Length: 76
Length: 41
Image 1: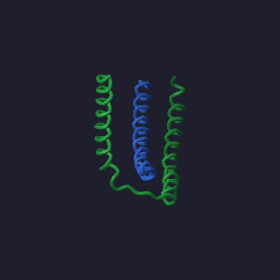
Image 2: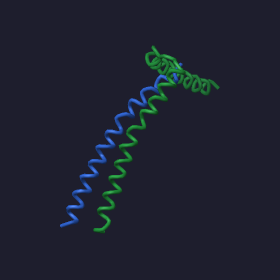
Image 3: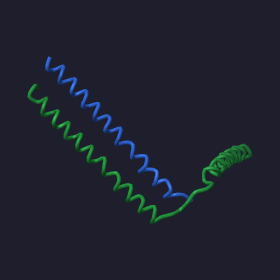
Image 4: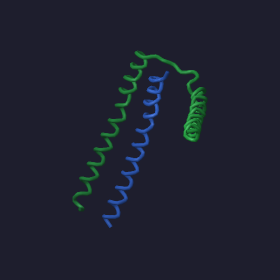
């Protein structure tokens, strides 16, 4: 295994060099995403504010429907 | 004795790789931030 230590270290340093090269690649993805955002707009103002209200009213509707089904079965 | 030196060198280069990976991870947030605007109604 002693003869493989320098070779393993050199391969490891080559992997580090490959990672350093990969570092530069993400700028291309960033530029492509910038181009996409130039192609497509859209904006958001009050989605999160009304999402909680929608969830609350949906839960209320679900509870009301469950109660309605239970009461219908009881009535029958 | 040489095995201990090899282990120390391997640990050092592993720490260097971990630092390189941490540096790589930094740009992921900037990459992902742009996608958020794409799909809303």
